[PDB]
View 1 (cartoon, rainbow, N blue to C red):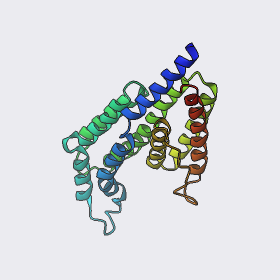
View 2 (cartoon, rainbow, N blue to C red; view 1 turned 180 degrees about the vertical axis):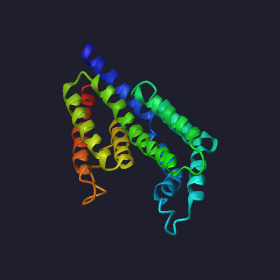
View 3 (cartoon, rainbow, N blue to C red; view 1 turned 135 degrees about the vertical axis):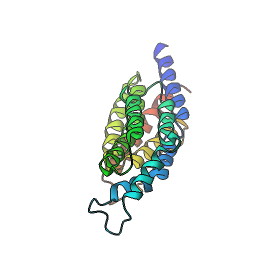
View 4 (tube, rainbow, N blue to C red; view 1 turned 90 degrees about the vertical axis):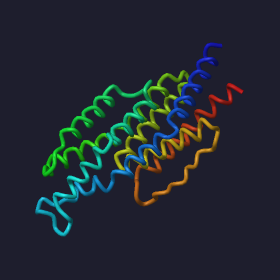
Length: 221
């Protein structure tokens, strides 16, 4: 009756969320890929004047690359948009604050550049966690208590995996959810044996979550 109907509503909300946010990991990679050299030129610049690693010129170009067309802010706003209905309240202001920092960044100020760079790095990890927060909200509404338990453990292991590599953790998270809601078997194969300690436990969390979601599905057709 109501329980069968609330199971279906929960499953529809998870699928709608996943499909709307299909490109979350790909789009966040694209930001990271475009701005890694600008980030590295800021970070590696040695205040010892540089040691055969160019000079203050490279930092100014890196900052200008970050500001160009407000591209990076727009790309972050695109990700906020994709989880509009579930996003943590902190995310919008964190993107705004970063956008303001970027306007304030002037030439020949390596400290400010490193700071702008540091807020870039934190925003990345924060945007990863906004996706986990978004799934946590959705999964917490589930009436099936076994799925909620598997979701709590999955979020836990997802968060620990994010501390090791935020963008790989995000990729595996988006893969697992996408597979599960498209009735594709989860691939529990590790791709980083003897590198990321938190991958195996996360893929285990994913298999148990698959188990609990399959079991709800079996009760709907």
